[PDB]
Image (cartoon, rainbow, N blue to C red):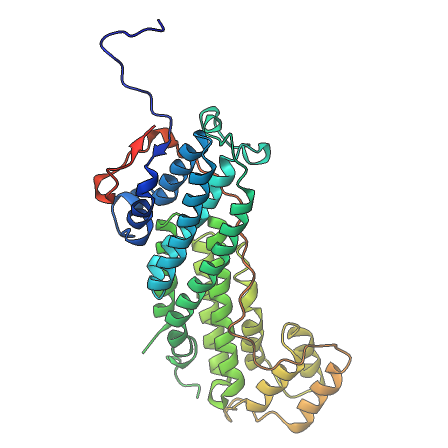
Length: 377
C-alpha cells in the first residue's frame, strides 16, 4: 500500500522533538533559564527538562545536523551555568538542577548507542539511540559541570546546617542531678534535605554521597567545639553526645542509608564522647584509652583530657601524670598531627551511570512550559 489511503492515519511518535534553529535561545530560555522548578509537570516526571532536552538532541542527530547538535549542547550547558549563578543560593533550585544535569548526562549515555551503556535498555529504548554523532567529549564537560553544581549544593546545605550543630548536639541539656536548636531540629532538617532530593529524583548513589558529606559536617563541627571549649568536656556531655549520635545512626537505618559511609564519619566524635565517659586514673585506664581511641590523634586525646571538667562527687581532675602516661604510650603510634578537623573538607563526588525506564515515545509537552513552537517527531 505505498500510495495514499483515506482516511489518513496519524503518525506514530518516535520520541524526538524538533525546533527551528532560529528558536534555540527561546527553547533554552523557557526550558532552563526561566523554568519554574516547582511546576507540576517537572515534579510529576522528575528530570523532565533533561528528557525534553535529550529528545531535542535526538532530532538533531537524526537529521545528521552537526551544527545544530553543537549549538544546542553549548546553549544547554551555558544556560545551566547561567541559572546556577543567578539562583544558586537556594537549596531547592540547586538540587533541582544537579538532578536534571545528571539525568541529561545519563540520557547521553543510555542512548549513545554504545553497547556498554545499552545493557538495561528495552528493545524500544534501543531504537532511540543516537546514530550519527559521538558525544563522548560533551559528556566529560557535563560531568565536570555536575561536579561544580555538587560543590555548590554542599555550600548551600552547610550554611543552613552550621548554626544548628553546636546548639543542637552540645548545648541543649536535660540530664538531672549529675552536675535555639535541638537534636530534633537537626533531624528535621536532614529529613527536609533528603525529602527534597528524593522528590527531585536525584540518583540514590548521589543522595548517599550528600548524606555522608552532611554527617561529616555534623561530626567535624561538633568535635571541633569539644576541642576548643572546657565546658563541653564532661561526663554528661559525653552521655548526651553518645545518645545524639545514636539517633543520627537510627536516621540512617530508617532511610536505608547504612551503606552511605555516613556513620563512619562520626567515629572520631563517637570516640571523643566515649573518652569523656571512661575512667581516667590508672595505668590500665590509660592503656584502655589508647586502644579505644584509634580514630583520634594523640593531639585530640590529650586536648580532651586537659579540658576535662570533673564533677567532684564522682571523679577528679585528670592528673598531669596520667596525661604524661598517655603521651608515653602513644609515642609508638605514628599519628596525624591534626588537632582541629577541616570542617570544610569535601569528599570527591562521582556520578555512576543510572539508566531510566522512562519511555521517550510517551512524553507529551505541557502548555505550561511555553514550548508550543516545538513539535513531536
